[PDB]
Image (cartoon, rainbow, N blue to C red; front, side):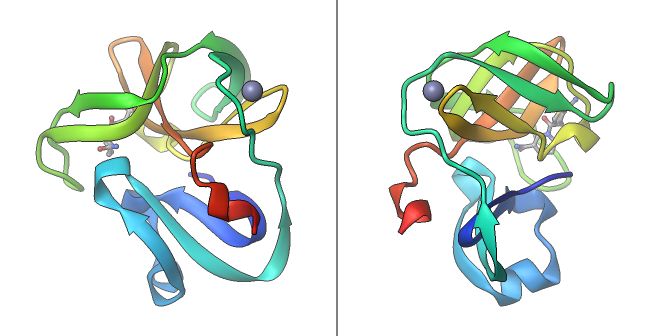
Length: 139
Ligand SMILES: N#Cc1sccc1CC(=O)N1CCC[C@H](C(N)=O)C1
Ligand SMILES: [Zn+2]
């Protein structure tokens, strides 16, 4: 679990969105596993606007932060789950690192701010949904 709070927005994994998130929906994209809902309180996270390929992510299954090198956002095949059939997930970045399903929502950060959130994993890899291209999150 986990979310990004920036301005009057809350960014979460679409497969983990709540009834309140869907009732206050701003935007959602199944192909990215992202959902953004509106909030009544101000968010203070800073979104990174960069092409960093190194950063640190929070891994709840280990209660630890890990430094990682990660790939540029791209279309990557993702095995079927109870949330989606087998498909290509877009704007996804992979890194070599530990992740378990409950790890979704952990933030990936670089020196410039929030890069994305954990969205996929397995076999010693971790995948992050990028949020750096969502320029509207800041206005
Ligand atoms: N094992 C393992 C890990 S680590 C983080 C998530 C997972 C499981 C995982 O990859 N998914 C299940 C939930 C939906 C995800 C998606 N974006 O389609 C796919
Ligand atoms: Zn950066």
